[PDB]
Amino acid sequence: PTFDTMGLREDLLRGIYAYGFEKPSAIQQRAIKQIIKGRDVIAQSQSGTGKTATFSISVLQCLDIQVRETQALILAPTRELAVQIQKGLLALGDYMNVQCHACIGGTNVGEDIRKLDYGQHVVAGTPGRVFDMIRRRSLRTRAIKMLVLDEADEMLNKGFKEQIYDVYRYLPPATQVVLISATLPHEILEMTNKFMTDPIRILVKRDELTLEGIKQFFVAVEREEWKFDTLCDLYDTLTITQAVIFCNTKRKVDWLTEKMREANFTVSSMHGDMPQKERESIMKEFRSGASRVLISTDVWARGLDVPQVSLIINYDLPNNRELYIHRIGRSGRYGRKGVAINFVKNDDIRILRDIEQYYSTQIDEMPMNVADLILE
Image (cartoon, rainbow, N blue to C red; front, top):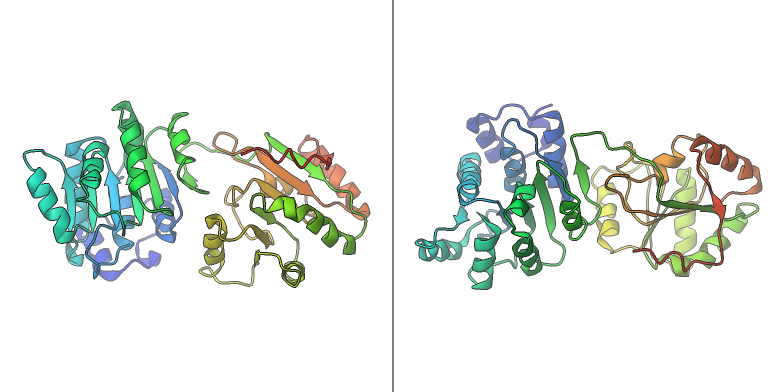
């Protein structure tokens, strides 16, 4: 596992190796790989090598040199550290002729603003100071596309709660937010889910899927051609939120998609026969709020790596009771409660029992009550 296979730009990879960082951790590779994809990330810091570089490498990669204006903003708990981040960023992109500044001083506020105008590609500073420069109309958020909250757990122990929040506000509507932190309190979560849609969590302790908190139901359709109507009947109350509708085969997604679109229905659809860059390209739309109903086959390899949408419709019960959970199960320690409606036909009223019996859970029949879809 190296930096070579990550398709990072040359002038950076040079800096990386020159900086001396020769091989990325197993997890760090994910962090990087994922931040680049654009996903919101929650990486738990661990006493080790360059927990700074890992995200710095990320930040740097995702830049537009030719456009001199603040594109990435990093907040840290201390002036000293804010600087480090800078000295490091500069050292990593020495070969990218990148402009990067750290805000603070007071005796320096003039030099502070002086540089912000020359156009700082990346800015770092304590939440307080950074907010000030934004308030003073000195720091240009307009083109910012990434907010990184380093040592966040600490930022809070030093009570920057509000300032952070305030800074998010000045940032544009869809902004990528990478939070780095050694610990994860019941309040850092309150912040993560408060401005991070379907984030990638990279933790230290095993977090595992479990369907506790999930309301599971089944709509006793009878045969397949009757499924469609049953879906529609539900659909106008569905888009209430987005929804991911599964399926077991390519031809069956394709069918369902076409059949829903010739009926005027905003629907995205992805399967296995597609590109590692168009697939995640659809997702972009979907996690965005740009598409309400996504119909797909089970493509995600990992368990947790499935959209944390609040409503999942197994259009087809899965034929091996160990992925029914893979599909609808949540995170437990960091998951959002939710719903999943199952479409079991007579030939499957059985497979349904096996699943119910397997996870030792209960799957009820859909009540008229869709008003139970009230939850967040």
